[PDB]
Each structure stands twice: as C-alpha cells, then as structure tokens.
Amino acid sequence: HHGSSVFHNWLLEIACENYFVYIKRLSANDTGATGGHQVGLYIPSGIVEKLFPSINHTRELNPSVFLTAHVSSHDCPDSEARAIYYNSRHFGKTRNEKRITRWGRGSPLQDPENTGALTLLAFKLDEQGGDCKEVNIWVCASTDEEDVIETAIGEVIPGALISGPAGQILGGL
DNA sequence: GCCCTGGCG
DNA sequence: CGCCAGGGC
C-alpha cells in the first residue's frame, strides 16, 4: 500500500542528480476538472527561461518543443509532452503564457481527482546547453507523501508556485 | 485529445 | 500572474 518510503527514495535520487524542480498543487484547470480543453499544465515563465531556452522568445508565433514525460508515481505510459510559449500578445492578440500539453488522457496530470494534489515535476537539465529533453513527474497519492515534502520545504499552497534546482529545493532532506 | 484562443480576479 | 474555460478540428 506504501506509506512514503518509495516517495522518499525517489526524492533522494532527484535531490542529488541534475534536476530542476517545479512543485505545485494541481489546479482544477491543470487536471481538466473544470471542463476546459486545455489538456495541459500551466507553468510559470521562469521554468521556460531555464529549461527551454529555444522557445523563449517572441520572434515567432507560439514556439514549442517536445520532451519525454515519464510518471514515476503511477504506472502510466510515457508521452511526448509539448512545452509551449503562447505569446500572441506580441502578434496583436492576447496570450502571454507557458504551458506543457500532451500528457495523455491516462496521466495523473490529466486526472480530475488529482486537483489539489501536491505535484513535483523534475526537469532533467541538459548538460550540454539546450532544452530539457525529459521530465520526471510525481503526483502525491496520499497525505503521507505530501507530508514528506511539506515537512522538508514548507506547505505548498495553490497559486504559490515553487521552482528551483534540486540541490536547493531538496537540500533539506 | 489537442490546437489556439479570450476572459476573470 | 495563475487560473477558468471552449469553439473548432
């Protein structure tokens, strides 16, 4: 059934490998619980600036790049997720935000019941200078797992996004 | 399922 | 800034 041992072990591995971490409570929109067709995750600007430089600009409309999404907390097929800069405010329209879509209908990131779930996305840094090519996801499945992270980094509050290099965010394990 | 879009506080 | 959607494909 798991308490939090497997979570903890995965955390230690992320903590000491070359990852940049994004931690949030999934919103109802992220998971699809709203009824909207976003089929993707809202991400803050700083994630793209550090992880996907090639898409970080306004000299082309809606640039995007692909990456492998692998879910570590759930048995779930991998997918080619798509990191996107919706930037139409520069092209005469209204959008100016970043997104990752294409998790798959069966992902915990597309399950309406994980709304409010404490999630951690571990982006694998490109040590050779380009775009992140891979993200490992963990959606906490219980309050037990939530306590491990929240004990370590403080409470995670909807809207209040946490991101940073693994060695810093998870240094307190 | 996913594209790209606009609106709300 | 994050989140709430949805027409059209």
Image (cartoon, coloured by chain):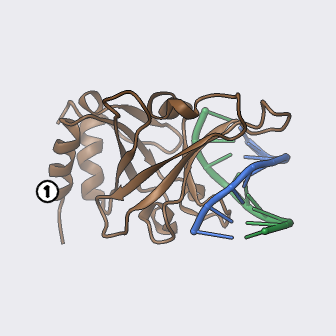
Chain colours: A brown, B blue, C green
Total tally of numbered discs in the picture: 1
Q: Is residue A25 above or below residue A172?
A: below
Q: Chain of mark 1?
A: A
Quarter containing the C terminus of chain A: top left
Q: Residues within 10 Å of mark 1 (few under 14, many from 20)?
A: few
Q: Splitting the image into 4 quarters, where does residue A152 fall?
A: top left
- Which residue is nearer to you in this view: A92 or A165? A92
- Which residue is nearer to you in this view: B7 or A87? A87
Element at label 1: helix
Q: Which residue is mark 1?
A: A5
> Residue sitting at 69 percent across and 28 percent down?
A58
Q: Give the image location of residue A69, x and y in percent.
A: 40, 55
> Residue sitting at 51 percent across and 34 percent down?
A48
- Which residue is nearer to you in this view: A110 or A58? A58
Q: Is residue A145 above or below residue C6?
A: above
Quarter containing the N terminus of chain A: bottom left
Q: Give the image location of residue A79, x and y in percent.
A: 43, 61
Which residue appears farthest toward the front when viewing the image? A128
Q: Is residue A120 above or below residue A125?
A: below
Horizontal side of C4 relative to A10 (left or right) equals: right
> Residue sitting at 28 percent across and 33 percent down?
A166
Horizontal side of A27 relative to A78 (left or right) equals: right
Q: Is residue A140 above or below residue A91?
A: below
Q: Splitting the image into 4 quarters, where does residue C5 fall?
A: bottom right
Q: Give the image location of residue A121, x and y in percent.
A: 38, 46
> Residue sitting at 33 percent across and 29 percent down?
A128
Check disc 1 and give the amino acid type.
Answer: Ser
